[PDB]
Image 1 (cartoon, one colour):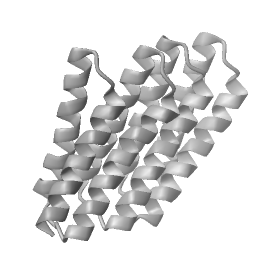
Image 2 (cartoon, helix red, strand yellow; image 1 turned 90 degrees about the horizontal axis):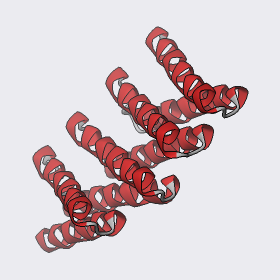
Image 3 (cartoon, helix red, strand yellow; image 1 turned 60 degrees about the horizontal axis):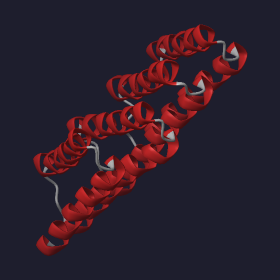
Image 4 (tube, one colour; image 1 turned 135 degrees about the horizontal axis):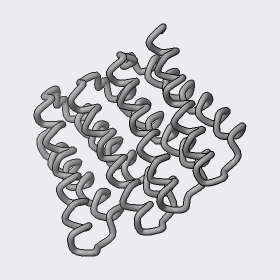
Length: 195
């Protein structure tokens, strides 16, 4: 709250400084940061996951995507907005599936960051990559709920397997988004078989 205000101000300063660095419009950037913050905050609140720690992770996601946008030739404001929308999708999936585990949520956010960073390196669209990462989480989460899997270890291991397949695709020069989506479908098949 007083922490939420301070966190928002930290994000605004980050997004604006990055826009200034590359000559993107700073008034647009300030507005984008503010709107990105509110999007994240409201999504987390609705999902019952608005701990300071989850909000910090969401803001770190936005920060890292924005910093890599400055290095890789992406519009700063659009990058911030896309990162925020990706978190919102994670929060929505968590809500729908009843996920509140801090370790699971941290892994889901890390997966988005990794898939988006890869896309930025390669010159691909941020939103498309973020959609693939968030959808992989959604498919896992929904499969776990459907199967009655309550274990945080099982869900962490599912997301780690997605991360492992994404990393392998990076080492080998294969499609990261396809790796993520295939890994999630493999988990879904196993969850359904279980229950």
